[PDB]
Image (cartoon, helix red, strand yellow):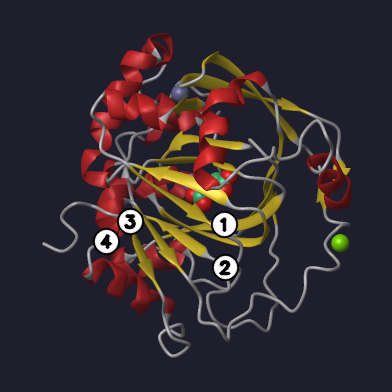
Amino acid sequence: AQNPNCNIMIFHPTKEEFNDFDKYIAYMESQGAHRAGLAKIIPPKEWKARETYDNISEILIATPLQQVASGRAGVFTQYHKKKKAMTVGEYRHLANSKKYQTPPHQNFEDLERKYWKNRIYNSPIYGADISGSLFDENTKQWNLGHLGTIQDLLEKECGVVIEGVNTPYLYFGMWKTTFAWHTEDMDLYSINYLHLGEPKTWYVVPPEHGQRLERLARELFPGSSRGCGAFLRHKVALISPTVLKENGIPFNRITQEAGEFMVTFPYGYHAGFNHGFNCAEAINFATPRWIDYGKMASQCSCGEARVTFSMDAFVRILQPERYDLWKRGQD
Ligand SMILES: O=C(O)CNC(=O)C(=O)O
Ligand SMILES: [Mg+2]
Ligand code: NI
Ligand SMILES: [Zn+2]
């Protein structure tokens, strides 16, 4: 078995190897990459997402989210308070303000310490889940706006044609902005490209050990657990590495820098934070290996997680028994 310790793998494809996305994903899995839940892909040196970032300041963040924390430093929840719209230029200036900027630090490890010690005492503002793309239309390789669609994968594998579309999303982050412990909708893959700015630190639990993280989460967030049988789908709970280590939960960590791709694998729980002002683009995708994960994916039926038009069809086709109760939560 390849990669039996489930370490995060880092790949350096040549420009030749960067032509066929599906094939490269299948290569990484041949080497065991999915066992970690997360992989880093460093693009060929010749490749670029676009020529410059010089004209992005007029993108609108219609609903910036202020991430307010409750709990203790290593075990907390966050709620998103909606703020007034602002442009990317306005947001960048805010991120660079004395109130919100990254503190002085020695290296990524010191910064990680400061994040876990101090996150809960601040409320950074995240420009998340903005439909759009920063890839130039002429970028042919690993263009997250030109990927094969999940609906087309389901059609190719299963023969059934369904409605729905699959488009990317932009994330504008600042120091301390946080992504809570989650897997993707329908336990899909995700791919995330860090277009610009400061790094993003990731934590991940191997898919084979996801239920260990779920059991810990039920113990640490016991009211949330009683409220919903899949409450990590709400994307609100944080657990620190120290706490995970105290409870024997297998995980790994890695820092993504600008210009790098990360891939999350089906049922790979992940969480993390941004080091400073940055812009990431991400999208879900599927492969044939995903289908079985999609059929087994948990679902939020309490009604909090409230998810896309396109997830309807996935549930309807892969999870027909759940169908019914799940759409009661989404209507
Ligand atoms: O970048 C973020 O805030 C969150 N991204 C992801 O969870 C992802 O790409 O799957
Ligand atoms: Mg602009
Ligand atoms: Ni994710
Ligand atoms: Zn729920």
Q: CA distance from mark 3 to mark 4?
A: 19 Å
First in sequence: mark 3 or mark 2?
Answer: 3
- Amino acid of disc 2: Leu
The residue that mark 2 highlights is 144
Instruction: Report whether the residue tagged 1 is closer than 8 Å to ligand 1.
Output: yes
User: Picture coordinates of residue 174 (x, y %)?
Assistant: 70, 42
**Mark 2, residues whose alpha carbon is within 10 Å: few (<14), some, or many (≥20)?**
many
Which residue is disc 4 drawn over? 289
Is the residue 95 above or below the residue 54 in the image?
Answer: above
Please state if 300 lies on the left or on the right of 214 as rendered.
Answer: right
Q: Are marks 3 and 4 in contact (CB under 8 Å)?
A: no
Determine which of the numbered discs, if any, sits on residue 282 in the image. 1
Q: Is residue 263 left or right of residue 82?
A: left
Where disc 1 sits, the SS reads: strand
Q: Quadrant of the N terminus?
A: bottom left
Classify 10 Å Cα crowding around label 4: few (below 14), some (14-19), many (20 and above): few
Q: In the picture shown, does residue 193 fall above or below 11? A: above
> In terms of image quadrants, where is residue 308?
top right
Q: Is residue 107 visible?
A: yes
Q: Look at 48% across and 25% down and name the residue there.
A: 237
Sequence-earlier tag: 4 or 1: 1
Mark 3–mark 2 Cα distance, whole angstroms, equals: 22 Å
Note whether residue 300 is visible: no
Number of numbered discs visible in the structure rendering = 4
State yes or no: discs 1 and 3 in contact (Cβ < 8 Å).
no
**Amino acid, disc 3:** Ile
Could you tell me the amino acid type at mark 4?
A: Arg
Residue 8 is tagged as 3
Query: Is residue 37 left or right of 129 when viewed as pictured?
Result: left
**Which dot, 3 or 2, sits closer to the camera?**
3
